[PDB]
Amino acid sequence: EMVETVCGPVPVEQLGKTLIHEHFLFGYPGFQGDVTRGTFREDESLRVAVEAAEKMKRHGIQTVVDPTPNDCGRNPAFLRRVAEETGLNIICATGYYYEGEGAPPYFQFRRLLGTAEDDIYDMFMAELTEGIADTGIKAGVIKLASSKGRITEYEKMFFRAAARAQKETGAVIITHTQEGTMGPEQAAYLLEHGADPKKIVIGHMCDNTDPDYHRKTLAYGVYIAFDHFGIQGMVGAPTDEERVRTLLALLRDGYEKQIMLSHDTVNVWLGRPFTLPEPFAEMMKNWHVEHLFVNIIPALKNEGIRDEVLEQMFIGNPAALFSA
Amino acid sequence: EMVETVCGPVPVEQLGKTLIHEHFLFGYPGFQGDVTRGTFREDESLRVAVEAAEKMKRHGIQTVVDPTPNDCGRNPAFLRRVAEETGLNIICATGYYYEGEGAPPYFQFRRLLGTAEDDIYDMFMAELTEGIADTGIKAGVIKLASSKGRITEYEKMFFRAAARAQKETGAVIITHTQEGTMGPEQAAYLLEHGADPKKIVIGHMCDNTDPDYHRKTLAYGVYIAFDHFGIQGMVGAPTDEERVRTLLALLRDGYEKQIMLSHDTVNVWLGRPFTLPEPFAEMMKNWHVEHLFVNIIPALKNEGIRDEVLEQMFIGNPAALFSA
Ligand SMILES: [Co+2]
Ligand SMILES: [Co+2]
Ligand SMILES: [Co+2]
Ligand SMILES: [Co+2]
């Protein structure tokens, strides 16, 4: 009936049109050490984050899931400010990123102590059922992530802890896959450990252009997310044209009740500002929160995708995902 | 001749008896993500850190160099609270840790952008000559660190930026070596990029028990630190008995003017509290700030080491190190 947002419990039936994977803030681990030159400018950051939220609202978005990992600058209190200003529902996560873009030393050390996996489960339970730090905000999803071609031993600790927490709480799991790998493997591993496929979203699935890879993942009964719309020009990433091609094939096969769409935007980068070099910068120009609504959805409609199917993906699926 | 401390400039002639490598606070990268169960409690932490400072003061210590890396929870304002309460001089660092206990994703990303090395130099210069964040505190040393058996491409960016910053500022460089490797290589690499050997301390040298490894390093004209006293059993670490054996051999060889001693304590751990298992816990029982004075120095004097030699290491060498 209810889901935890940054403003507290909200009825699942009130979530409405949802973006399943966007970041208001995000930083690569290590950004914290560059505080002198890469200061967090909260006022400007809030202005930018609120502007992004308003752009989403303009296209009927009422809810956003922000799965910023705990080790990547997650800031629930900041999200609450965005939500308070805009009236958007924002659902945050508990979880760590994958090894290559994460900060593994801490839980690797606890693994040497023999307690890491239990500590992670304890962290998930605390943040799902008690609150994050002193904010009073509970996470509404568990974020999991794996490496390219491998769910590492470090990563598997989180996967097992997540399955355990899910069995206890009924919490939704949202995942990151790296470079179009491990979708089927994540689903199989989570299900081995008793996780509920109807509560799992395997992310970044659109990074792989082989429809058989998607169908192998869909076979487990999980949700999949095409959540990289706008990300073009590598590393390895396919084009939006290719993403649309893959999506159309799955919709023709009747998989709409298992698919959600997003952009995985980073609206405010933590640390120093940066500029992409020009070939890449132009290829990435559509990576913003309006892209699905201005470009992608019109293209789907051009191919004959019905409004009810679009509504299934943006409204029906998040409602079902967060319902018992 | 002055050095920057957490309280501002202090005459080098007033540093007196110094511990070259101790941490009031330290966290393994990723500790930030375990904030809920591992919150930093400032009042209690300050009480503990102040007590550690008072323990050092009782043995005549007037100065501590705290080289906590930027990515390992460095908190200069906290150090200033400790120093303001106790009158201890505390000198802090600018730098990142080695890959295996560091947070490389941030500067790895900036390396891809082509700016990392310049960004690191910029950071070093800002923190040595202007201030850290909004604290008004300047770092007095640059902290460098390498991995086991190699200085990685990531680490080398910091090494080159450090040499550049040293040429400009005359700043002292303090290093970490991993598992008794890369001592000579660090010295060679820094001098090859124009760093001053009389301003370099190669750290954790006591983790290697081969006196030829030490003599190879010492031949570069650099300082070396036996800075792991009390750390026994963990990750290939030698015993204190073995450390004393190596140290005695070098002192009898006439190397006193190049050697400094410390414990590399962590007085307050960031993140969740932990307890070491029973075999390791007993082995680590002497890992505290009084150990050199209560146990090690008496062991050295029992082996014929005179007060003048000890004073050279604890007083003479730090004064020379920080002098032009
Ligand atoms: Co991701
Ligand atoms: Co993401
Ligand atoms: Co070290
Ligand atoms: Co240290």
Image (tube, coloured by chain):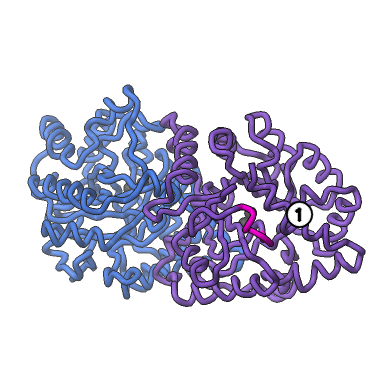
Chain colours: A purple, B blue
Residue A253 is at least partly visible in this image: yes
What kind of residue is marked 1? Answer: Asp
Residue A13 part of the magenta segment: yes
| Quarter of the view holding residue B300 | top left
- Horizontal and vertical percent position of residue A104: 50, 45
Q: Which of A99 and B197 is in front in this view?
A: A99
| Quarter of the view holding residue B131 | bottom left
Residue at left offset 29%, top offset 40%: B228
In the displayed structure, does residue B233 sit left or right of residue A88? left
**What chain letter is assigned to the residue under label 1?**
A
In the displayed structure, does residue B156 sit left or right of residue B318? right
Q: What stretch is highlighted in magenta?
A: A12-19
Position of the C terminus of chain A, as image quadrant, is top right
Element assignment for label 1: helix
- Horizontal and vertical percent position of residue A298: 83, 70
Say which residue label 1 marks.
A207
Q: Badge 1: few (under 14), some or many (20 or more) residues near its Cα, within 10 Å?
A: many
Residue B218 is at least partly visible in this image: no
Residue at left offset 19%, top offset 70%: B9
Is label 1's Cβ within 8 Å of ligand 1?
Answer: no
In the displayed structure, does residue A29 sit left or right of residue B190? right
A267 shown above or below A161: below
